[PDB]
Image (cartoon, rainbow over all chains, first blue to last red; front, side, top):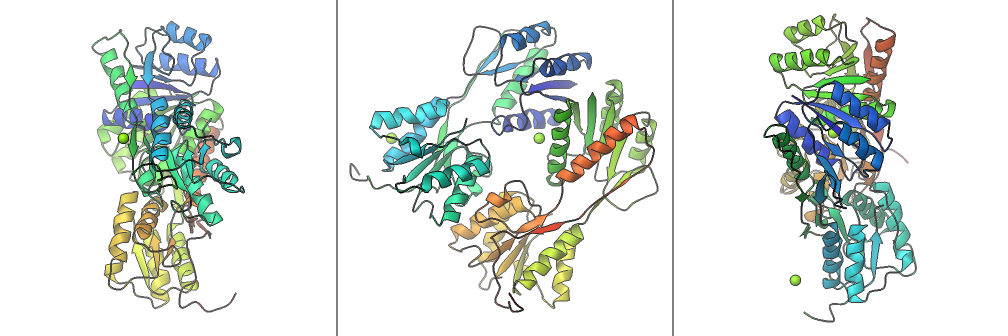
Length: 276
Length: 276
Ligand SMILES: [Mg+2]
Ligand SMILES: [Mg+2]
């Protein structure tokens, strides 16, 4: 009773929560976990692949940022060992299980809550895209220009959000609201504002994305887009099961929908002049 | 290379930060990790053991909170497999490696710092230790008495720190500083002080324990005790890599020392008056 788990990075703030879910379920079902953590290397990922085969694991489970031809090749050579390939976005007619998170709808929702709160001068601390694409469509649809000097890439880690917010806030003209593409990154943004002497949400409104466990325990309690992370691994982990037992060779798609969690990091903006 | 890890719980406060350092070191070398959480069932651990032997892991890391004779005996059968069996707890004359975290010392440094900064009416949010004990000695030694109404425990998680902080802060009379035995928990206390209109540390000073990865980016930047978890993880790993090749049958002692990290959550107390 063991299961392989070939990841792209346990420590990749994005994925991470998913793993914990795959994990806690295994222990919960007293299985053994055989953790492989690649990082995009045909051989390393290969290595990890054969080893789980030799340790005769009762199920596989892949989580990959990409799925290039080579990887895809290997993956087939090991079809005898039952699995679940979590493939985000691009539903390519292969044999991978499609994960549809509705990030595009996620970012949409965020950018829209801000327009509705009356903000028109907006900042964005983008991660390393669908979300973002979502946010620009509402900005576009509302005719809000976004100065390029108010768009600063983060990396999912607090120091990046800390450096990003300070860059944005530290300009003659600044926005009244900032869209943060990651709750963790948003924790580093709340800090910088505070250290600069800015009252959040009073001087700057902030909305993040994820709804990480601690997000409600931020100061202030963080308004964000709840992205079901630890629902995905439990499902993926169940698709693995049925697959090994019931012999479910026919694939499945895991799709979720985003939801806005209203809390306390967002205030009314100056454009409450237009409507009530 | 495959490495096996037997632990009571991967998700337990103390271990959590230790297991991730291990994991991080594994993937760095390219090793695979075989994870198992046994929880205290002689039988279940006795099952993970046989299987790991069966999967031919190159080495074993054992960390268990308690090692009853019977666990120790079964481990003795598997001594052909290189292992590091971490033992917190009173050093015994057996093959276990000793782990010495100097918690009582961290607790004391914490108390003392508070007392030095001028506070005398202190509150406490203990975890479900020896740190608490070392904390109380710095108290007892400065004649300070800490009332029961100002002691409320948590369980490592944020809501627990929130609820206890609210409880202590809602007292007709309140401490001027609080000792939180765990940063995560402190994350919650910090949010609680805020939602009650109290400013940290203008109105209340706060000190945590651990110095978790994000602490510096808490709001405000947290004053806490750095308790080394990553170093321990690193240390055990390397000891295991050593035994794998330099097959060493000599128990080792791992000692770490806590260190105070002065950030921005603690201010001068009323009784502060010894210098600048
Ligand atoms: Mg983990
Ligand atoms: Mg509506």
